[PDB]
Image (cartoon, coloured by chain):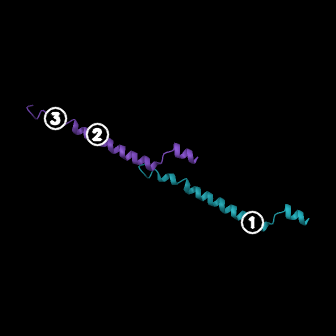
Chain colours: A cyan, B purple
């Protein structure tokens, strides 16, 4: 059961770190696309 | 998509330069013809 524990289980102190990371990466990427999809709006400020 | 971007797209900062150029060339050429079509009117100021 020790062996199967180290194989099959997850230590949640690691998991929650992975979660915090991934959540930051998503909220980031979303907020990034808020800008990437607005950089083409600099176009029609020029000559329109 | 990078490759197809550099092939098929236009960088608009180049385009708008081409536009400004062409517009100047048209407005110019028009205003030029305002004179070229009036140089023959110097004729009938002479002997009529």
Where disc 1 sits, the SS reads helix
Which residue position is annotated with label 1? A16
Work out which residue is located at the far right of the displayed protein and give it. A1
Q: Position of residue A25 (x, y in %)?
A: 66, 61
Residue found at x 73% / y 63%: A18
Instruction: Single out the residue that lies furthest toward the top.
Output: B48
Q: CA distance from mark 1 to mark 2?
A: 71 Å
What is the quadrant of residue A23 in the picture? Answer: bottom right
The front one of A4 and A30 is: A4
In three-dimensional space, the C-alpha distance between marks 2 and 3, rounded to whole angstroms, equals 18 Å
User: What label sits on residue B30 in the rendered view?
Assistant: 2
Question: Circle 3 sits on which residue?
Answer: B41
Relative side of A33 to B15, left or right:
right
Instruction: Give the secondary structure at mark 3.
Output: helix
Question: For numbered disc 2, what is the local secondary structure?
Answer: helix
Dot 3 alpha-carbon crowd within 10 angstroms: few under 14, some 14 to 19, many 20 or more: few
Q: Position of residue A30 (x, y in %)?
A: 62, 57
Q: Residue furthest left?
A: B47
Q: Quadrant of residue B24?
A: top left
A5 shown above or below B37: below
Disc 1 chain ID: A
In-image side of A8 versus B25 (left or right): right
Q: Nearer the viewer, mark 1 or mark 3?
A: 3
Coordinates of residue A42 in the picture (x, y in percent)? 47, 53
The disc at residue A7 is none
Placement of B2 over or under A20, stated as above or below:
above
Within-10-Å neighbours for mark 2: few <14, some 14–19, many 20+: few
Chain bearing tag 3 is: B
Q: Residue at x 51, y 51 (%)?
A: A40
């Amino acid at each position: 059961t020790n062996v199967r524990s180290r194989i099959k289980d997850t230590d949640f102190a690691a998991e929650t770190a992975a979660l915090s990371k991934n959540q930051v990466l998503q909220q980031a990427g979303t907020a990034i696309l808020a800008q990437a999809n607005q950089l083409p709006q600099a176009v029609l400020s020029l000559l329109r």
